[PDB]
Length: 128
Image (cartoon, rainbow, N blue to C red; front, side):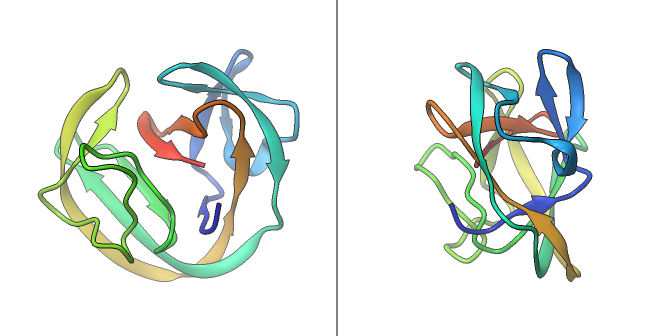
């Protein structure tokens, strides 16, 4: 997929939490449906970034096209993901988006995973 995540975003492997900048092809990352294999690590890219903050405090930084599962299907900021909609947090609990804050241009990275193409990122369910 298009878009990307902050380098310091944490994902859960069987060997513990890893920053996504350290993920390699063949790693396993936890989703709502078990561990998905990392099939690709696409090139790092500089993009405008956005911070999403949920009502439980959890945060994630991503690009405008990065997708998240919602009750209406996958959505991104460019496609109208906004405050007052809910994301899923570990384990499939709905939490309101309190804020979406545009930040700065920064390096981001993008991976592809197997299975349902999802993984928990800072304990927020996200699409690859």
